[PDB]
Image (tube, rainbow, N blue to C red):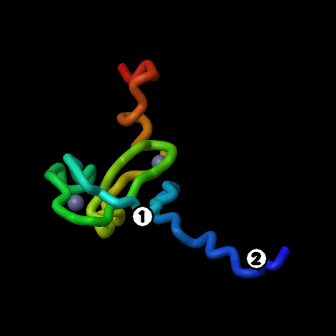
């Protein structure tokens, strides 16, 4: 395919952080406070939200969904 430029290089600790458009009540899963930004990041596998710069303190993407999955025996 013509997509000979796959920028598959956006993994800090296993989570895929994609740019979102925070326009409402949002909280930084890395700074435990309200994201007053117009852009944030989300892991499609652990459903976190961060200030689009606090991803270098988020745990491995199998140590985030171990707190962000309300359908697991997390006890
Ligand atoms: Zn933050
Ligand atoms: Zn994740």
Where residue 35 sits, quadrant-wise, is: bottom left
Q: Secondary structure at mark 1?
A: strand
Q: What's the CA distance linking mark 1 and mark 2? A: 21 Å
Q: Residue at x 49, y 55 (%)?
A: 15
Q: Earlier in the sequence, mark 1 or mark 2?
A: 2
The x, y position of residue 39, in whole percent, is 31, 65
- Extreme residue in the right direction: 1
**Going 42% across and 64% down the picture, which residue do you hit?**
19
Establish if 1 lies above or below 49. Answer: below
Disc 1 residue crowd, few under 14, some 14–19, many 20+, Cα 10 Å? some
Q: Which mark is residue 3?
A: 2
Q: Nearer the viewer, residue 55 or 27?
A: 27
User: Do labels 1 and 2 touch, CB within 8 Å?
Assistant: no
Residue at image mark 1? 19
x, y percent for residue 17: 46, 60
What is the quadrant of residue 50 in the picture?
bottom left
- Residue drawn 14% across the image and 52% down it: 33
Instruction: Please give left or right for residue 1 compared with residue 10 in the image.
Output: right
């Amino acid at each position: 395919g013509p997509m000979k430029e796959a920028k598959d290089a956006r993994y800090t600790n296993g989570h895929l952080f994609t740019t979102i458009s925070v326009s409402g009540m949002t909280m930084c899963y890395a700074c435990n406070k309200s994201i007053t930004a117009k852009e944030a990041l989300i892991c499609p596998t652990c459903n976190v939200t961060i200030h689009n710069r606090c991803k270098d303190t988020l745990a491995n993407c199998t140590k985030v969904k171990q707190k962000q999955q309300k359908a697991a025996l997390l006890k």
